[PDB]
Image (cartoon, coloured by chain):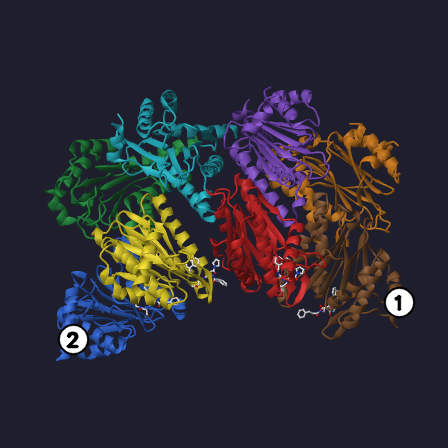
Chain colours: A green, B cyan, C purple, D orange, E brown, F red, G yellow, H blue
Amino acid sequence: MEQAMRERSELARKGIARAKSVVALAYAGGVLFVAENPSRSLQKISELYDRVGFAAAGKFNEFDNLRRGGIQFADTRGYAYDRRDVTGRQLANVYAQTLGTIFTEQAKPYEVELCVAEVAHYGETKRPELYRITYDGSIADEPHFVVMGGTTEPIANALKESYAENASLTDALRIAVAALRAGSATLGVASLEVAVLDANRPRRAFRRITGSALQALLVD
Amino acid sequence: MEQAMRERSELARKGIARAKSVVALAYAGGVLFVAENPSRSLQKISELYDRVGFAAAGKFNEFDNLRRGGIQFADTRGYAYDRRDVTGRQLANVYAQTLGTIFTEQAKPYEVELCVAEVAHYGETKRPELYRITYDGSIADEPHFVVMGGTTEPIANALKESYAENASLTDALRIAVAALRAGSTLGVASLEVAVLDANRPRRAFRRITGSALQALLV
Amino acid sequence: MEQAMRERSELARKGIARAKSVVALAYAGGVLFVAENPSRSLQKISELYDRVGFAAAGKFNEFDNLRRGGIQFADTRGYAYDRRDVTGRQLANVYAQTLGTIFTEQAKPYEVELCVAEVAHYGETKRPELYRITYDGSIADEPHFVVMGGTTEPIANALKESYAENASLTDALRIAVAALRALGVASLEVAVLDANRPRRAFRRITGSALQALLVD
Amino acid sequence: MEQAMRERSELARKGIARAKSVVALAYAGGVLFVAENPSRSLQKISELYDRVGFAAAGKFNEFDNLRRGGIQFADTRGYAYDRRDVTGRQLANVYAQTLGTIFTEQAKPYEVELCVAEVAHYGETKRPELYRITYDGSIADEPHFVVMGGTTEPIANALKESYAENASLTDALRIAVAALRAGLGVASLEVAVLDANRPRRAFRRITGSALQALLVD
Amino acid sequence: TTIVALKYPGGVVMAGDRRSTQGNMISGRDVRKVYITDDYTATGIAGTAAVAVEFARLYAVELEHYEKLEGVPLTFAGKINRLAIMVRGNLAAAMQGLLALPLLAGYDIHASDPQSAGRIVSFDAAGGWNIEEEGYQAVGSGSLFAKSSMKKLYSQVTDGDSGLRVAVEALYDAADDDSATGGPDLVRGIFPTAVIIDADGAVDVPESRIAELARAIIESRS
Amino acid sequence: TTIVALKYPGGVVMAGDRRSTQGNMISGRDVRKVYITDDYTATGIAGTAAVAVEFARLYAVELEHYEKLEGVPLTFAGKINRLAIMVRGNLAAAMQGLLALPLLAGYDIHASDPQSAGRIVSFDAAGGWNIEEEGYQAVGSGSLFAKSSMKKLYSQVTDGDSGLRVAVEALYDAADDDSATGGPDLVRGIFPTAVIIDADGAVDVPESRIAELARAIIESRS
Amino acid sequence: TTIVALKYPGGVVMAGDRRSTQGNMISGRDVRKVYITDDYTATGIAGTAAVAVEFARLYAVELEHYEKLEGVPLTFAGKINRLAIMVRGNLAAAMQGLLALPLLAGYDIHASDPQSAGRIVSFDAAGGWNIEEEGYQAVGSGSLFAKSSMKKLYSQVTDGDSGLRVAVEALYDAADDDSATGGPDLVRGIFPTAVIIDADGAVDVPESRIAELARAIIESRS
Amino acid sequence: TTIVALKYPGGVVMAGDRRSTQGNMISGRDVRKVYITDDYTATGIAGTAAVAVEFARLYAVELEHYEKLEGVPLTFAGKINRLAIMVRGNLAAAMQGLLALPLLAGYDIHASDPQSAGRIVSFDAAGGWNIEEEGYQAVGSGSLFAKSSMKKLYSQVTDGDSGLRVAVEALYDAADDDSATGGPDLVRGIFPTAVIIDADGAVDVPESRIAELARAIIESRSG
Ligand SMILES: COC[C@H](NC(=O)[C@H](CC(=O)n1cccc1)NC(=O)CCc1ccccc1)C(=O)NCc1cccc2ccccc12
Ligand SMILES: COC[C@H](NC(=O)[C@H](CC(=O)n1cccc1)NC(=O)CCc1ccccc1)C(=O)NCc1cccc2ccccc12
Ligand SMILES: COC[C@H](NC(=O)[C@H](CC(=O)n1cccc1)NC(=O)CCc1ccccc1)C(=O)NCc1cccc2ccccc12
Ligand SMILES: COC[C@H](NC(=O)[C@H](CC(=O)n1cccc1)NC(=O)CCc1ccccc1)C(=O)NCc1cccc2ccccc12
């Protein structure tokens, strides 16, 4: 069973290293998600709940199952209690429990790695929260940014020298695309998936930046 | 059978030894929990029942499962009978039975080590109880302190030399961070602290964070 | 199969040998349970029913499961029929049955050894009964004493030589601790099935009283 | 798969060989059960139904389960139909079926060897029947005696030479203990008879002073 | 139906009538309502015949089952409790008309006093039970006439024979005032059935003995 | 049926009558409706006898069961809660006629004041309960007469002896106004049963003390 | 039964009477109908006592269960939704006679303005809820008399103390017109119970204060 | 109760009264019966309050659930179908006294002509639906008074402002003939609530605007 656990861990690790990278970073306006994504309709970054967003790297069907299950959890909880009782830490916690179970009991572990981000409710003063859940269910919250998928250390190094708190949307996006560019082995609008949790939106904070708007923000 | 149970205990032991350490000690006012924890929001220390607290080392999702089940058990027993029928011994026993089953029958044993602590009810005179439940369901009675996670022997030895009964909150906290340093430099931002305070009228668990915690470390 | 069961039997035998020892003796007043138990709140000796007591050696969570299961059996049987129909022999029988199933079918066998003891009902004259049940469901009816846990041969030898029938409480207690050393309050857990009590015979002897009976 | 089966067969045969021995033989008054048994409260010989008795060798908890299951079957059938529809043959057959199932499908085979015996109902002239059921569910129809557990060959050898039909109770008991010796006293024996002369329940234990009076004198 | 049970020095007697009815129609006259349920216990049941006979049969099976499984018979309290649980189990069916009320008579071998080892237990439809301290009891449509007859006659019980006589006479007074209870049939020679229990066990009373006590009663009241 | 229970300094006392009825008919004279359920607890139950006894037995085993499993007895509040749950469990059966209301009397070893350690708990058919601050309580068809009697007699309760007198007198008034409640039978020598509970536990009050109290009242009312 | 709740600057108050009835008969004089369920929440319940006490107990358990599982207490909206789900859950049993209606009083620590953070929530038998914007509310058989009384007395509410007074006077008017609501008993010294909740949490009002306020009202009406 | 909804050029409006009743007794005066259920749909419900709010809440959750799971909101026909399925689901309990009838008002962004993209859907207790091609609809105990009022006043609808006014006026006629429907309370300042939906989305109309139209109608009948 040390055999089985090692082999499963390595299957998951190699599965994520082979996958495109995703970056999530806190900025003055909330949380920013940038991912390497050629597709027009298949999406690695998603809304979970009012002030809670989701990002994933790895095998699409697997992290999509987790995204849908996460939405089911958030919607059921918000109905059972109140929308304001649904929190980032809760979704990060359920994912840690779920992926722990999957990693230990499914035929094959999930080759996925997750980020749950939460911004404050409209009119409140609360620092963004970012959570990183790994394939075996390990969970860690990071204060500034999270990187997932592919070769992480070049991207994380680029950010840890490049990152400044309270950046502009243009500044945070530019540093983010630079850090992603350090780890790729050819990017632009057609090659990116971008979305933000906007702490200024009144209720639903998740909003996408596509096409002309994205191009205007990348030229800075 | 022999080889496989050996393999389970080795997997669990190694998982715990890779994990940051947590210490729980009895002091003049009740029970003190100090854990090495950089996180701003994820908990290794928690309330179980009125006079009962929980601390853990190992895989978060697993000791979190056990924490929730403990709360589930306690709230159910208190409802079926009465709040004063919930005891620390009962929760420690249910954890022993649970980890025994998990260790022998689940796909993977839980990489966890648990501590259940109980202080007296308000106005009553009872000395705190500490229980260690390990990954295989073994349970142990401790009167003074418990160490879990990471490199245990340096921490346990530092406490064996520096520990005194009925110390004040500040002194016990100082001892705890010292012993924690000996093993796996430690401020508020890297520590999680809470007490079972026997002087609270009903719910004894209480957190000491931020301004209060720094105020105690000086 | 034959190899797998030999391995299970060995896992049980080794696990039980690593644990602390427990002794049970018939004496003039009923049955005496003496166990090495440092714990203040975890107990190796327990009451099962009015005149039936339970003692165990080995892994705590496992023989505690068997203890709770026995109390459950005894109480439902007394309710379903009558209190007087609950007997030691029948509890020993369900323990043999249960440990047999555990030993053959559970993920891991139980690293435990059990003693069920029964004294006579108030005003009746019956020699106490002692039953040993081992990890595989083997049951043996023993007339004078039972030893369980750890290295049993020294303790059983000490009693075999030193055992006296119809001993006094102090007499049987001192023979028992003597054999156990082959040990103060803090290190001992002691209780009796006291055939002189009117219904519930189980009596714990703790602290001051126990100390009083050891020092003489 | 056949490796698993020989392993089970040898585990059961070894377990039964290490256990104590039991003999049941038909005599003028019915059937006599005598078993080597030191215990004072644990039993290897039992009543199943009005004219049917049970004896077993091997591991106690296992043949005790089988004994209760037989008692359940007999009582259930007797209630569902009528008492006189319960027969030794039928109990022997269900034991064969049960033990075959155990031997192929349970975690560990049962280390048991079984004897189901039946005498005639009161006032009828039927000759007693003995049935042997082995750990794999094999069933054998026996007319004179059954020996089970431990080293069977010497006791059965003593019986083959010493057994006579229609012996007296004292005589049959003495042949029985004599055959057992090849392989003692009240404290070491358990005896009971299926007594064809009792009107309803033929099973009857012979204990203590009565037994001792009946051994030699 | 009337079933009587009474204590005498060192034993108990139980006797029951033989009449089976469907409304006003007599559908049986040789019916047995008193059964030996074990070596020291007898049960008589009143009510629906299907349910009464089912009770007696299943109860006897239950007691012998326990005895063979556990090597020793149930204590008398256990016997009362299982019969009580059985009645309460039948309560729902009894509400829709399938009622069966038992009366239990036994000799307790594990009792302290050998001549106070007699036991008489009556029940209610819910399985309520009563161990009767006062020497006699009855059940059935004639039970009140029988109990009032025994209230005057019980001082005459000095041995098994007098107890048996009082028993038969209470059955006579029962059938005398209750048409559902059958009196002695002298044309057909059918008489109440009776069971006696002492330290030697429970035995059926021979038909001829009850016949001559009945003839004694009839003769004596004409 | 009448069951009374009252607090006295340092203890509690509970007493009950001996009558069993089926409508107007007396089906018993010696029944016991007050039971020691625990070393510091007694229960008296009114209503259908079968359920009243089943409640008593099952409750007593439930308490001992918890005690043997967890090595310590239930808090007094826990005992209240388990009994209440038992009543509510029976409500459906009670609405069909199998109703039984208990009255609980205990001594709380975990109370601060050794003279406020007596506890009297009354219940309703839904399991609602009341811990009685005002010193006495009763249940049964005579409970209203008994409570109004205790309303006038309670001021003279200073110890267990006087408390037991007030109890027997309250049962006497209840039997005086309620034909379903049985008074002292001086020809048969049958008297109410009582349980007294103090710091030393729950003990049955012997017959002789209750009889002399009875004759004391019977004398005083002539 | 009558329970009142009213908002004052910076807080809220809730009060309940002490009377228990079975039809027209008084079955209790000291019952408690208002409970601290949470550090900033109190609940009063009207209806069947068994169901009401179970509600308050079970609800407090659900709130603290959530808080220990998730490290933060429920938002006030969540608390309301859970109480409503509990009521609606009982709707069938209520239709059969086990009816219990709650009234919820709280202080919302997450409200924007700390002086207007007081909250009053009423429910109906299907679990309908309404958060009251008009300052006061009531429940129980006297709720109409209390609501009409507070309609005239509410203008005098300027702080916690005056609010507690109009609450007690509303319970006085309720008891004055409704026999199921018990007024202040000056012979036994039993007065309504009240809870105050403000920014510093939920505290039980001392009985002596309520006794004072009761006597002020009684005097003022003589 | 009365809830009205009507189309105007380029949008739709929904308004509902504030009264809560139990028999003849007024148990509420400020109750909200008209809800924003999604960025381009509003729902008003009539009947038993517990069930009515349960429906609105669950229905909004169901729509948003679909949208987050599938990256696109439901088609308007799909929304109609889900409300229908919800109502028929409740028909058994509704038969026993737990009735809730909804009215749906929305703006269909996938409509052919944005001029006529407004939608008004009424339902019955079996979950039957009607997409209204005559401009207005109402539900509740005052719905026939309101519909008969709008039959005479609907010709005056030329923009969002006149349409809102006419809606409040039909709610006024309903409250005038139906005691379970609450009219404008000029002492407490409680007025019907209304939601307006156009291409810019669905917004709740500011209470001041309802107070102005209410007093406007009251004087319109005092002179
Ligand atoms: C008092 O109640 C009248 C009762 N009669 C019945 O139950 C008779 C018995 C009868 O007539 N039998 C005819 C041949 C088979 C029996 N049966 C019935 O009355 C039918 C009951 C029924 C009606 C409608 C739907 C379902 C069931 C009775 O006589 N009972 C007396 C009685 C008591 C104990 C053992 C008995 C054994 C045999 C016969 C009678 C017995
Ligand atoms: C219902 O209030 C009257 C009640 N009478 C009954 O319950 C009597 C008791 C009786 O007569 N017995 C005779 C032998 C066994 C009991 N029982 C019945 O009346 C049975 C009612 C019933 C009929 C059909 C279906 C279900 C139930 C009563 O006396 N209750 C008093 C009482 C209280 C506590 C313990 C008791 C124990 C024994 C006897 C009485 C006891
Ligand atoms: C309005 O209705 C009257 C109601 N009364 C009851 O419910 C009374 C209270 C009572 O008499 N008790 C006796 C000791 C224990 C309670 N009980 C009953 O009315 C019995 C209900 C019932 C009857 C038959 C079948 C099923 C259920 C009442 O007083 N309600 C007020 C009330 C509210 C909150 C908590 C309370 C706690 C205790 C007592 C009352 C309480
Ligand atoms: C139409 O019929 C009258 C109906 N009234 C009720 O349903 C009232 C509302 C009420 O008085 N409340 C008290 C505060 C919270 C609710 N409730 C009831 O009438 C309870 C129904 C019931 C009776 C018996 C058993 C079970 C249930 C009503 O006014 N309905 C209007 C209405 C429509 C949409 C949303 C609403 C939201 C809140 C309040 C009312 C609402």
Left or right relative to E121: residue H59: left
Query: Which of labels 2 and 1 is toward the front?
Result: 1
Q: Name the residue under label 1.
A: E215
Is residue D4 in view from this perspective?
Answer: no
Left or right relative to C106: residue B158: left
The image shows residue F205, relative to residue A16, as above or below, that is below
Q: Which amino acid does label 2 sit on?
A: Ile
Crowd rating for badge 1 (residues with CA inside 10 Å; few <14, some 14–19, many 20+): few
Q: Which amino acid does label 1 sit on?
A: Arg
Secondary structure at numbered mark 1: helix
Q: Which quarter of the image is occupied by the N terminus of chain G?
A: bottom left
Is residue G78 in view from this perspective?
Answer: yes
Judge by depth and name the residue closer to the eye, E5 or A57: E5
The answer for which chain carries disc 2 is H
Q: In which quarter of the image is residue B196?
A: top left
Q: Mark 2 points at which residue?
A: H218
Q: How far apart are marks 2 and 1 (CA)?
A: 107 Å
Crowd rating for badge 2 (residues with CA inside 10 Å; few <14, some 14–19, many 20+): some
Secondary structure at numbered mark 2: helix
